[PDB]
Image (spheres, coloured by chain):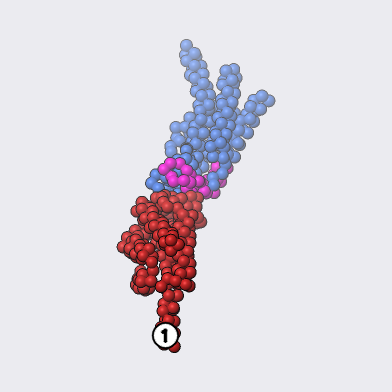
Chain colours: A red, B blue
Amino acid sequence: GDWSFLGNILEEVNEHSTVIGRVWLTVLFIFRILILGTAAEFVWGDEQSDFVCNTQQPGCENVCYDEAFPISHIRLWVLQIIFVSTPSLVYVGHAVHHVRMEEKRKERRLEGTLLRTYVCHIIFKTLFEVGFIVGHYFLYGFRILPLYRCSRWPCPNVVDCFVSRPTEKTIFILFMLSVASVSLFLNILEMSHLGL
Amino acid sequence: GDWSFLGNILEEVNEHSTVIGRVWLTVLFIFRILILGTAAEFVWGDEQSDFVCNTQQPGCENVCYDEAFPISHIRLWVLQIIFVSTPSLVYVGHAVHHVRMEEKRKERRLEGTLLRTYVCHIIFKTLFEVGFIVGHYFLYGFRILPLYRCSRWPCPNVVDCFVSRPTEKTIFILFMLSVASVSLFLNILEMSHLGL
């Protein structure tokens, strides 16, 4: 996973953001992207290969892994990162559009419409963070148990399947939840600081 | 299985029985013992070796075969044969005891106490036949289905196990039931013929 493109564009908008937005962005780079690439990706690497079911039924392990894990937590966190970063991109686009307009108009900072855009970007970041948190909760909760019982066809009756590294995965699930909540708190502080 | 001993003793009591008792004994030799040794024993030969369960759990097939088949039908029919033959042995013992007494008393047929003994032997044969029929019914019924579902420990949840030769076994179960019922009818005819 090469995050160079997103990185370069978000460090562009480091220069154009509040101090609390610079903290938010540093958190995104260090506690989410870096963790994902240096730790979480390896934890989930053998998610299906080490998933085992007590059965001689061909196909059962496939369908039971798929039912237990409709989308891997790591893919969900990738999507979360991209969607929470998208409003920053929108804002920096608006800002650069104004810089190029000012240059052109001459040929021919957080005030006015850039403030409304910044506040909206904060709002959307907050809502997307909340949405991904809630979705994670309803999909998986915040704990992976070792045992998963499966009755999906072709599995005969109910079969016992065993998850890879449930405890390490639980630790990283809770870590990512905490990081997301810190991000939410930072966004709240941004709104308060702007208001006051 | 060597039935020579029992055979010789029951062909001793061929000579001392009614015509209907000679028919009963011929039925015992031909339709029960001979069938058991020339046919049924081979049908049940691979009862556990070809019994298969859809599981990777060590021990499960053992406990599931044992729960499905607490006692093989062939062992049950062996016991049935011996118990229904036992009263004939008692009667012939009484008769030979009287023959040896008469010989001794000289040194020094179905009348009197031999009639009471013969009738009692018929009664006990009837009751044992009925008891084994009823026991067979309650234990297994009169049909072996291919699928047996098992939840005995160590089996995880419910496992699907598959029986060897369920249809051939059902055919022989019904055949042996019919032969037993014919034997019952013969005993009833014996009692009627003696009464009339």
Q: Is residue B154 magenta?
A: yes
Count of labels in the image = 1
Q: Position of residue A9 (x, y in %)?
A: 37, 73
Residue found at the far right of this picture: B196
Q: Residue at x 56, y 44 (%)?
A: B143
Badge 1 element = helix
Q: Which residues are magenta?
A: B146-175
**Image: B102 above or below B72:** above
Q: Residue at x 45, y 35 (%)?
A: B4
The answer to whether one can see residue B47 in this image is no
Would you name the residue on which mark 1 appears?
A106
**Figure quadrant of residue A129:** bottom left
Residue found at the far left of this picture: A38
The amino acid pointed to by label 1 is Lys
Query: In the rendered view, does A191 fall on the left or right side of A34?
Result: right
**Image: A162 above or below A124:** above
Q: Is residue A33 magenta?
A: no
Q: Position of residue A148 (x, y in %)?
A: 44, 51
Q: Nearer the viewer, residue A49 or B112?
A: A49
Query: Where the N terminus of chain A falls, by quadrant?
Result: bottom left
